[PDB]
Image 1 (spheres, chains in turn green, orange, red, yellow):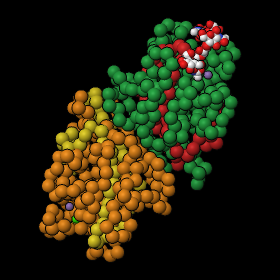
Image 2 (cartoon, protein in one colour):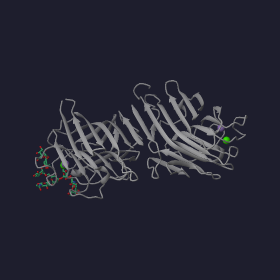
Image 3 (tube, chains in turn green, purple, blue, brown):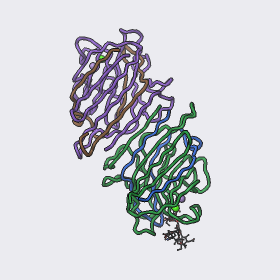
Image 4 (cartoon, helix red, strand yellow):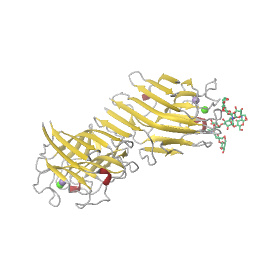
Length: 181
Length: 180
Length: 47
Length: 52
Ligand SMILES: CC(=O)N[C@@H]1[C@@H](O)[C@H](O[C@@H]2O[C@H](CO[C@H]3O[C@H](CO)[C@@H](O)[C@H](O)[C@@H]3O[C@@H]3O[C@H](CO)[C@@H](O[C@@H]4O[C@H](CO)[C@H](O)[C@H](O)[C@H]4O)[C@H](O)[C@H]3NC(C)=O)[C@@H](O)[C@H](O[C@H]3O[C@H](CO)[C@@H](O)[C@H](O)[C@@H]3O[C@@H]3O[C@H](CO)[C@@H](O[C@@H]4O[C@H](CO)[C@H](O)[C@H](O)[C@H]4O)[C@H](O)[C@H]3NC(C)=O)[C@@H]2O)[C@@H](CO)O[C@H]1O
Ligand SMILES: [Ca+2]
Ligand SMILES: [Ca+2]
Ligand SMILES: [Mn+2]
Ligand SMILES: [Mn+2]
């Protein structure tokens, strides 16, 4: 057994246990990943590496995470690109911005990526997003083209609470977004 | 609120959430800090910083840690120097070895060290240790001369379980060592 | 009121290294928006 | 089963920075011993709202 847990309820000016990348900073009790400025990237990572599976044993971890985020856009139509909760190699640095959401660099599976990310995607990139053109939740394994997606209506400026859980016995990864209105 | 927790029941060979310093490393599910070898120092630090107090609210944190450890001397006489659990600045580096337990450098209070340590001292150093010569548990703030001591009889090669708890409301630090 | 859920079987062990770092990313391109996180909780356990 | 307990009032915010790292050390010198740890558990909690 190995367990890692932490909770930050109000982020504060010198939040030393987070690694900030790109334009991530903490400000006014929030973790601000991007400002409403065009073409930036911001990322933030928990400081400790976590052990997700063991080679000796074949054992994979069970985990759960929840967080509440706010996407604040200029208006409901000019919103982009999105947000992601990702799991990546320990030395992960920002990847391609724009519609690649700073985690990936391609629409085709790339085993080198080693990144699993749940995305809250607000912009339709015709080359890889679902043909309905909707805003959406998705699970990305090693490519920005999601292996599954659910359509989502963005409520601009509202807080959304998200729970993501992984059950190692069944390998099911589950994500729930709830707008408290 | 801010919380930080972890548990490691058995240390693997690649224990990436710990920072190793001096001779520390993991071998056969144990974390080895020193080997039964002369003059070394080993430290292992948990990788995240811990928000222990806040200058904006003035609030301090409550915490508990527990660990099982073993000292394994050549025999019950020739044993030195001891082991430490410490809280230090995020950039902490090994300090002087020997009787300073790789964590202090002076017998005299140094406010710039900014470390408090709970030690389990198995060697008597005339210059700052309990004159009774006993092995002992001590609470050290910024010097190797503890502000408080308790005698403790070392059972060589035996697993000791310790609990260290800090109560922010009373600012009391409690240490319990029990041999099964 | 409004909730959304997604479930997939993603054998994590087949894609990611044994030790990983977790966190958040957000980008803007030709269009933009502020993306901010208000709190975060995480817990994992490997037998 | 034999135990030793020690208590001390030590006002931490006087002695440590706001952000710290915790860990173990062990040294040997002229005299020596192997020093190992077999397991470790930790939990901290800061109100930064109340006090506890
Ligand atoms: C069909 C066509 O070819 N049109 C060309 C475009 O190719 C050309 O550039 C691109 O524009 C894309 C969008 O084009 C829009 O306009 C055309 C016509 O005017 C429309 O046909 C088209 O459909 C687009 O409408 C925009 O569409 C989106 C959806 O696609 C709308 O959002 C929503 O859409 C849904 C469904 O349609 C629904 O309707 C919603 O209500 C609606 O709001 C949007 O409203 C509408 N308006 C605009 C202004 O487009 C861009 O997507 C494309 O890519 C960049 O931006 C997106 C979004 O942020 C990123 O996801 C994408 O990855 C990329 O990000 C980065 O953008 C910056 C800035 O452009 C790039 O940086 C520049 O790059 C240069 C080289 O490329 C240099 O490096 C330069 O230094 C650097 O600053 C950066 O490279 C991008 N990064 C990456 C990884 O891609 C791209 O800009 C446009 C230009 O005017 O002209 C069209 O005619
Ligand atoms: Ca997109
Ligand atoms: Ca000594
Ligand atoms: Mn997508
Ligand atoms: Mn002493």
